[PDB]
Image (tube, rainbow, N blue to C red; front, side, top):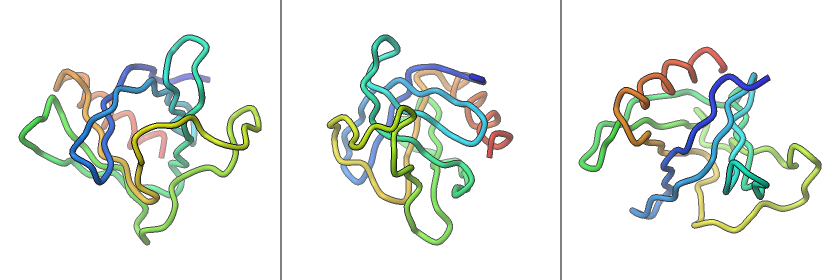
Length: 117
């Protein structure tokens, strides 16, 4: 039931950006290390999120996914029941900052995200 799938650049508290494979389908953003034989990193539950644009210095196009009550946006278990996620740079409990490599790509993602919410 995939709606969009692409590499996206993701950051947390740290200034560092990590390029990860994200699959958008109804209700969830699924994050993997690779498109192919991906190790599951985490799943964002869109039901718990709001989305806002986040204009910035390293931009491409930049937006923010967050829990309005600053609670967890993350699914407890993997799409295949995976107990624990693959190691990445530490990501925030209650938000993701996201930029697509191209601004036009970023805009489609953001617009797409609003629907899947």
